[PDB]
Length: 56
Length: 215
Ligand code: SF4
Image 1 (tube, chains in turn yellow, cyan):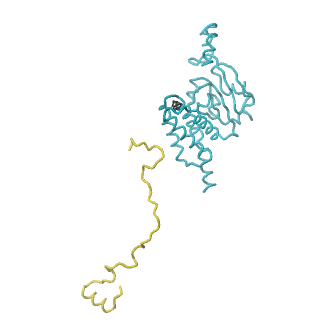
Image 2: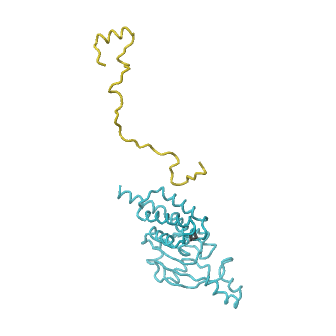
């Protein structure tokens, strides 16, 4: 947050809490909007043998 | 069968008791044997029914090429019977009940021997290709499943598969066997089952070699 030190002190005293530790505006701490590809594993029924549907 | 028809006049002339004198109970008479493959003297010979396989091979076929220790596997009753390794062929007899007990079946008493110098997977795949080329195509299990097994065995010969596919091929063979119009499907399923049962480590080794050299 681009806030002056005096204004930060005034708002901290007025609220009674330290605002800088828990800010309500998002910043660079959030994840990138471009992500690597996933792999997404398969479920338990993807076996090649001993997988007859009548048993599940 | 031709042999069944041809032995009948001799049976009538000499009596059924004479014919039943040979062989064990429920396996009586004499049989024609065709020994072929990796033997010094491949040949056709008529001999008493319940002869030991090793004794027949040594006495009439001249022994296994390179000696008895050189033996790798035997197909005892034609291409439709599962293979057996040396440990089974050591002390097995040649008749219906004893060969069924060895999980093979007497079949047509056509002995095809293979020494330790032959690709057993290649031989089984060639047999499966024969069965693919010989199915009449009437019923779907034989037609589609034998085509499928032929493709899978062709991939197996190179190791292009994964170890999990061995059990899948076994299940495919079971799905073919007992579900077809005639016994050609059974005769194609049994050699695959025998090859898996007696040489799964070789198939896995081939798969590992292919994966290693293909990465
Ligand atoms: S199992 Fe017999 S009837 Fe069925 S497709 Fe094969 S050869 Fe034809």
